[PDB]
View 1: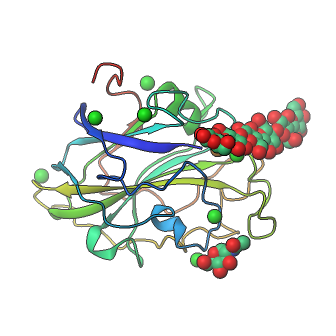
View 2: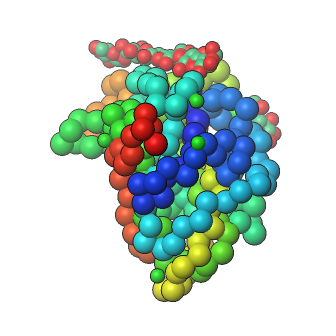
Length: 235
Ligand SMILES: OC[C@H]1O[C@@H](O[C@H]2[C@H](O)[C@@H](O)[C@H](O[C@H]3[C@H](O)[C@@H](O)[C@H](O[C@H]4[C@H](O)[C@@H](O)[C@H](O[C@H]5[C@H](O)[C@@H](O)[C@H](O[C@H]6[C@H](O)[C@@H](O)[C@H](O)O[C@@H]6CO)O[C@@H]5CO)O[C@@H]4CO)O[C@@H]3CO)O[C@@H]2CO)[C@H](O)[C@@H](O)[C@@H]1O
Ligand SMILES: *[C@@H]1O[C@H](CO)[C@@H](O)[C@H](O)[C@H]1NC(C)=O
Ligand SMILES: [Cl-]
Ligand SMILES: [Cl-]
Ligand SMILES: [Cl-]
Ligand SMILES: [Cl-]
Ligand SMILES: [Cl-]
Ligand SMILES: [Cl-]
Ligand SMILES: [Cl-]
Ligand SMILES: [Cu+2]
């Protein structure tokens, strides 16, 4: 149970984005139904009045929280991967439009899931803005919590992988458009009951055998990390 509070750009807090530049749902409940339109940008997908301006090569940091800003972020039980996708805003997230910019699942050195790392990062994880066409975009940050993913929602609707999905409205201003955005996958559609990483038992299967759901990260993606970039108590 987690939500995005706002974003930072190059380590500068853009301010509370809830219902402003984030297409915020009304609460932190998960999405579980893989075929639902809620998979696109959660349960209240609509245009919100602001977009955050960035330039290619900028660091865009999502900041998540549980109840209040910079709290415990998400329950530590919610082990799982984190991804970020991008689509053009003109799509409204419909169609084969979602391109993966970032994936982190299980880190064998530190023996930590992405979610664990996110808590340590005070809710912050980033992507570097790619060299796509200037214009308006949706960045879709997705946390998958696997604590009840040994069942499939489609078979048992009280269990299933949980998706915490947040779409940010981002305007890319300066960019030379040298890596124009390739085709995308659909949400809903990309994840199905047979997709690797959707049904998994994190209690009896070693985490090293976990494979996150495709698609793979776009070759044109410029990187990203789960790491604190700014201190919410000060700015
Ligand atoms: O040798 C070890 C053996 O381990 C076995 O594996 C076991 C393992 O031992 C055990 O840890 C595991 O137990 C998990 C359960 O299966 C799973 O269902 C459970 O789900 C919890 C979850 O931990 C918890 O975080 C979650 O809390 C929700 C809550 O439901 C929700 O209502 C609340 O909502 C509020 C919002 O948070 C709040 O912001 C808002 O204001 O109000 C909302 C409404 O009040 O949100 C919280 C999260 O914040 O609830 C679920 C239960 O619903 O997680 C357990 C793990 O902690 O089971 C494993 C299998 O039994 C191996 O199988 C064996 O081989 C090994 O030998
Ligand atoms: C899952 O979503 C699909 C598409 O909206 C819908 O038909 C189906 O009824 C949903 N499943 C449940 C259990 O609500
Ligand atoms: Cl839960
Ligand atoms: Cl603010
Ligand atoms: Cl759902
Ligand atoms: Cl708050
Ligand atoms: Cl950190
Ligand atoms: Cl550029
Ligand atoms: Cl579907
Ligand atoms: Cu939860």
